[PDB]
Image 1 (cartoon, helix red, strand yellow):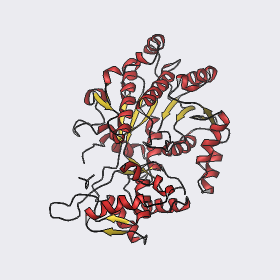
Image 2: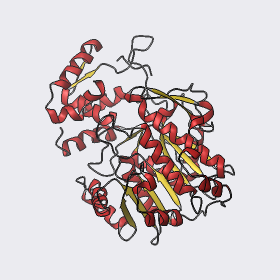
Image 3: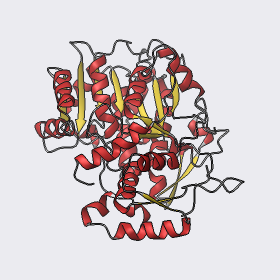
Image 4: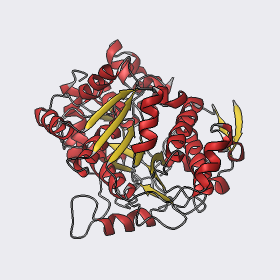
Length: 429
């Protein structure tokens, strides 16, 4: 348990003085993105970013993916394996997109030079036109990279972005960055260093993800101060599996574990939320977005280089802002109405203690995939995080399905039922 100040996350603590001094005078980057470096390709959002970035590259484009592995071919197999989820069309689509344009290299972004050979590192510094940093897949508790190695990895990527030629930098962040912040200060335009100058590291497994992402944003703000490096920060809410391909889930995230838990225990509460002022089921909204939308938004908006501002730093709140009354209770409604073996326990006190107990009664393999590890708690109190810049950009860049009146989508029943479908495909239900 220790305290970190944004002011101590200066680039000179990770990058040599010569590189930093030279970056000041480098010109703005070329808007033409032919070589893209992607981290986190084996993670859930990363996989969809692989597809979206390959679709956006030309026949001469190249996508270079850094993957933790024993060797470059081990890395290639690990990444290819994540697209082998029981959907023949996904594998077919991936292979055709990747052919002659996907390069997978073994490395650890938290290590010096990304754990890469110096010839490879130098080719990256000389040829990469765009850096995309997404969340790598961590299947063990607490399901994310610890603060130290994560900060080290962002700094290493910034080193590449600052060497030889400046490189636009897309950074996947999280709504959780705003947890320690009054909502009226937590805007897309605010400088993270001003509104969130101090944070506790190791302050509970829940807050570890937000604090590690906070540190990356601070380092990118420092890079942007130094040389106007074009940066695009995407603070994402919960990213949902969707119906585009079968078998594609983030097994580590809370929603996947909760759907498994509800189905395996068979018991749901009357409401996950405090009753409203009349004692009724409270109007609530869950901030989730389908991964296909999120990946497409990040790709389209992260490619704004010629149209980046003069100062060059953009933050987008990739969040579902709707006051639509679609929250966790409606997700449970949909599962029950689909005919799944879930019953509600009307007394909430009865539910939470029977639910935690029922999880401990599951077979070992299910227990590990449930919310029980995260348990080992009260009704939830239910639009505060502004999305003005993201939502306006969704309309202008025509992100998503509807190219006529584009807007941020809502969550609908097929997405929720599809979690059960995928979990059954995996043999976990």
